[PDB]
Length: 129
Ligand SMILES: [Cl-]
Ligand SMILES: [Cl-]
Ligand SMILES: [Cl-]
Image (cartoon, rainbow, N blue to C red; front, side):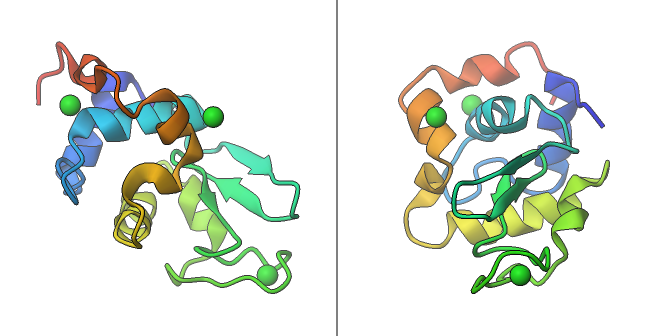
């Protein structure tokens, strides 16, 4: 599913992501924009052989099981395929664990490089929330 911008903001809020660990909704929408362009089915293969999955490009090295990332963990206790669903529940619940892991949203390199320090509220501007 490719979400609309406000549609995704609303779904993220529904699932308790808004201001989670102090990160406003615009941060999460911005991260999703640059990680996946709002596409739940996004996948990307990393140089180390791990894969990033879903709207927030969650990585199989630590967070989910895909059966093909040697030496990896599955800390969200989910198959990586669950992160590709039209229902963002699994991605949100896993993101909550990731952002609580110590480095906040810096876990998402694209958030650090493209969202951090910017006017992230622009991502939810106009949205009925
Ligand atoms: Cl915001
Ligand atoms: Cl594996
Ligand atoms: Cl980047």
